[PDB]
Length: 186
Ligand SMILES: [Zn+2]
Image (tube, rainbow, N blue to C red; front, side, top):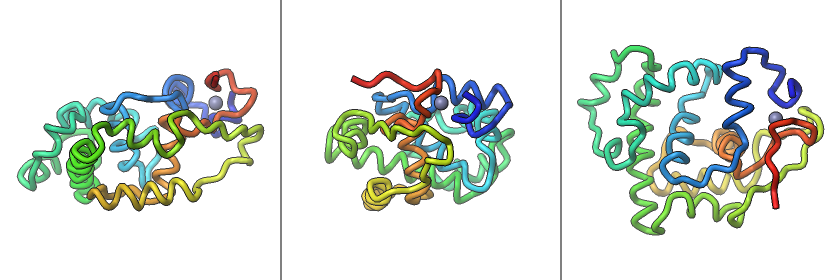
């Protein structure tokens, strides 16, 4: 559904809308990767990051948190000229701080997935949208999660960005009622 996919026609973006965005994601490492890539979105089109995903994977150990968490200024120095990623130093540093935060969460709570999913009581919040104009960009839960993640050292993940992540990972289902890609919830 065109309306649901923000009126974007580029089929690389539509692929993301159709096969990733809003589909419940329960795997800890996959959640981390999606969150990390979401943090790179700011001030750019999502298509920009999508086309660079494989480059980010090569830059960041396939977003494996134990490996990313150990990266240093020395790695970031190198990555500032690594081809086909966005060379915004604070964005790149943020991915490392996020990986460190993930490890701290898993130390305290066991599972990064269980930590995040707890914010919606273990099942997707169906926002029951019918029109694209129904959509909000932030809420109280995303704001609290943003704050809570900040306490474990996560960076570049403000309330609006976290809200976007919740929708992307399917913790929130923001697909329109008549979108072919709207997931079934039981
Ligand atoms: Zn949709």
